[PDB]
Length: 36
Ligand SMILES: [Zn+2]
Image (tube, rainbow, N blue to C red):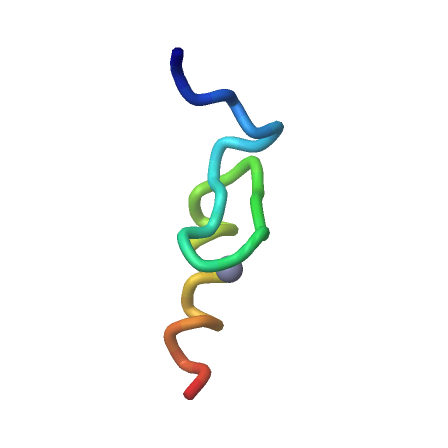
């Protein structure tokens, strides 16, 4: 078979976060980047 649409286009590579805009995901991925 093949992968589904997962309800939203931009699903985070680390967590269950997802959004309808790539710039909004990019802002969420910056939180994962700065957290240490
Ligand atoms: Zn995330």
